[PDB]
Amino acid sequence: PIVQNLQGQMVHQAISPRTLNAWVKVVEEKAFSPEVIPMFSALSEGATPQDLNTMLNTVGGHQAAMQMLKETINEEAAEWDRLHPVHAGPIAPGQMREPRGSDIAGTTSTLQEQIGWMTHNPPIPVGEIYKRWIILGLNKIVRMYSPTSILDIRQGPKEPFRDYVDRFYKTLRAEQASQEVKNWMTETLLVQNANPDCKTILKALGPGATLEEMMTACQGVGGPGHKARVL
Amino acid sequence: PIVQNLQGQMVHQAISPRTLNAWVKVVEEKAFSPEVIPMFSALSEGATPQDLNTMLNTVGGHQAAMQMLKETINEEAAEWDRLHPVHAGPIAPGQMREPRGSDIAGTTSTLQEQIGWMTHNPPIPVGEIYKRWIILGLNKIVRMYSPTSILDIRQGPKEPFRDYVDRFYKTLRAEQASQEVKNWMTETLLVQNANPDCKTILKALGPGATLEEMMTACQGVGGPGHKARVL
Amino acid sequence: PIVQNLQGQMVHQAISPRTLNAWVKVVEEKAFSPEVIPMFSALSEGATPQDLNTMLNTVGGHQAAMQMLKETINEEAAEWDRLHPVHAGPIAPGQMREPRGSDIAGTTSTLQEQIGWMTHNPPIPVGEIYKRWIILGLNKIVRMYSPTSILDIRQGPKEPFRDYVDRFYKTLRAEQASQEVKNWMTETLLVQNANPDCKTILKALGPGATLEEMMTACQGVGGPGHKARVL
Amino acid sequence: QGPKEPFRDYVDRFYKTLRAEQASQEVKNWMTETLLVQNANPDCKTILKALGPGATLEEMMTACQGVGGPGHKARVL
Amino acid sequence: QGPKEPFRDYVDRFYKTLRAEQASQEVKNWMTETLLVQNANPDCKTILKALGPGATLEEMMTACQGVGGPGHKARVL
C-alpha cells in the first residue's frame, strides 16, 4: 500500500508475503472467530483499495462469505453513488475526477487513478471508506455463523461461573446492537439463565454490581446465599 | 507506535505481524502465566494507546478477563479525570487542547489526534499511563485465575519439598503484596506448611541461614526426606 | 389554582368538592394501581403548592407511601437548591425575592406571597417542578407496589393468549424503563414467555411482524393458538 | 406484629397511629426510627437490623417488600 | 471460635494472645483483616462476610452487638 512521507512523498508498494502467510494461517486456524476483525484493521496501513481486494480474493474455504461480503460492498457502493453528494456532469482539465460508487473498488478503477485521488491534491478517504464497508460486512458475517443465540447461553449443575461468562463473551460480538442498551440487557440476562444454586449466590451479590465486583465474588468459594431464614 | 530517531523525527508505524503472531501464540500456551507481564512490557516499545487497544481486542480465549481489564482502564481514566489534571476546558486557538481522562484511551480520541500532541509538543505520557493501566489489569487478571491461597498450600504426606516449593513460588508471584512482608513471612511459612519428614530435615539447619544455604543442604538430602531418629 | 385571562387579570379560585371526592374515591378503590398516575395527572389542574399539598395530605389508607413520597419531594428539592441555580439573597428593594428549595414546600411559604412571586413579575416554575418531583415519588411507589416482574409472566398450558398478553401489558405498566431500552427488550419476551405450542405459531410467523400484525394472527388462531382442528 | 402477620399490616397500623401522635417533629423522628425495629415480630424484625444504621424509609421498604411476611407463601387450592 | 462460643469471648483470647507476640504496628493490623474472617465460627461468620471490606472496629462491633452470642439465632419459631 502507500508508504513513506518524512523521507519524501509517498510510494505505493507491494503487499507483504509475511502478512499474506499470516492472513492464510489465521483463517485456517480460526476463520469465523471475531479476533480477525481488529487484526484486519491493524495491518491495513495506507489502505489502498486495490491491495485490500487481494486479501478478499485470496481466501480458500469460506469463499461464500467473501462473495456475500462483495455483494454487501456493492450495496454500500450504490448508496455512495446516490445518497451522498456525488458529482453531477463535466469535470475540468487536470482534475482527478471525483469517484463514483463503482470507482471506489478495483473492478472499474485504474491504479494510478485510485492513487491520484488519494494524494494528488486534497486526499479522498477512499481506503477508509472501502475498509469501513469491509468491517461492516464482517460484523454481519459473525452473526450469520454464530451457533448460540443470547438466550441459548446457559449454565448446568456442574458448570462453574468461568465457562458461563466465557460463552457470553464469545457470543457478545454477534449481538450487534446499541452499546448503552446492550449493557442494560447484559445484567438482566446473567441472573436469568444461571443454575438455581448459582442464581441464589448471584442474587446475594444483588443489584448495582460491576464486572470486577462480580468477578471478585466469582473468585471465592461461594459466599452466603441464605435459604429458609423465615421458615 | 511512534518510532525512528537516527534517520530523523519519529513516525507512527503499525504493530509487527511477527509480534502479533508471537502475542497470540504465547497466549495460546501461557494464557495466565506471570512472564506475560514482562513480555507485554517488552512488546510495547514506542507506546501508543491506539495500537495498544488492538492488542487487547485480538485476544482469543480470555475475552472475559480482558473486559475486566478494560473496565479497570475506564475506572483509572475516571480517577484521572477527577483526582489528576482535569484540565480547564476552554482554550485559545493555536493550542492542541490536551488529553482529557477519557481521551487517554482510544475510545473518545482519534488516531492522528494522539500522534499530533505527542509530536508537536514535548512527550505526552499517554502511552506510558495506558501501559501502566494494562499492567495493573494483568496483575488483577492473574489474581482472578488463582487456585490456592497462602494457607491452602500445605505439603502432601509422600510429596517432596521440590514440588511444593515449585507451587509456592508460582503462587507467590500472583499474590501482589509488599516485598518486606513476603521476605519476613517466608521464614515461618515454609516451616509451618512442611510435612513431618521435610520439617524434621528443614529444622536441622536451624536459625539465621539464607535461601542458598538452606537449598544447598536440601539438595544433598534430596527426596521426600529420609526416615527419622527413632527406628 | 390561579385562573382567568379572557375576562382580565388572573385570580385564585377554589377546587370543586366533586374533584376532591373523585380523588378520595380513587384512593379508596385503587390506591396502588398504575392507573393512578395518569388519573392524578388528569385531575391535578394548575400547580400552586398549597392546593397540591391538600391532595397529598387527604390520603387515608397508604400513609407510609405518602410519607416516602413526601421525603422524595424533599430529596429532589435539596438537589434543586444546590445542583440547579442556587441564586443569591441580596437584591435591590422592590423585588419579590427568588424562592429557594425549602421555600417551595407548603409548610414553608405563605399563600399570599407564594402566588405573588409566581405571577406579579414574569413566572417562576415553582409549581411545575413540584408536580415533576411528585412523579418521581410515584415511580418509587410503583416499585414498592410491584407484585410480579416482566420475566415472571409466563403463559401456562391452559392459559389463553389474550390472558397472557393482558398480563404482559399489565406488568409492562410497572416496567419502569427508558424508551430506547424497552423498544429493544419487549421484542424477545413475546415468544420467550409463550407456551411451547404457542411458540410454534410465533416462530412460523417470524421477524417482521409489528404489534397490529401479531395481534391479527393471534385473533385468527383462537384461544392459546391450540393444535386441534383449527387449520 | 402478630406471629403470622405480614409486614404490611403491621406498618399500616404503625403509620395509622402515627397520624394522631401530636408531638414535636424532631423528637418524633428519633422515636419513629426505634419503633420499627421494636414492635416487629422476631422472624420479620431481622431484616430491619440487617440494613443497619442510617437507612431511609425507602431503603427499609425495599427489603421489607422482598421479605413479605412470616413462614412460607401459599399454594393454589 | 467454636459454635458454642460468643464473639466477646473469641475477641478476649485474641487480644490476650496478641500482646505477647511483640510485633510491628502494620503487620498486626494487616493480619487482623484476614484473621477475624478466617477463624470465626460458620454461623457467626456470615454476619462478618455480609458487612465485608471497609469500615472500622466500632462499626463492626456495633453490627456484632446487635446479633449477640455465637452468631446467635434470634428467631425462636
Image (cartoon, coloured by chain):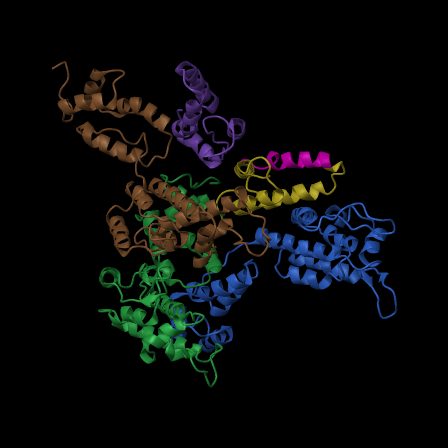
Chain colours: A green, B brown, C blue, D yellow, E purple
User: What residue do we see at 15% from left, 17% from top?
Assistant: B228
For residue D40, side relative to residue A65 (left or right): right
Give the x, y percent position of residue B16.
29, 55
Give the image quarter of residue C37.
bottom right
Is C107 within the magenta? no
- What predominant SS class does the magenta segment belong to? helix
In this view, A72 is above or below A19: below
State the residue lying farthest toward the bottom.
A89
Give the x, y percent position of residue D9.
61, 45
Give the x, y percent position of residue A219.
36, 41
Is D30 within the magenta? yes
The magenta segment is: D26-42
User: What residue do we see at 17% from left, 21% from top?
Assistant: B217
Q: Is residue B112 or residue A140 the one in the foreground?
A: B112
Q: Is residue A72 or residue E62 the one in the foreground?
A: A72
- Residue A214 in view of the camera: no
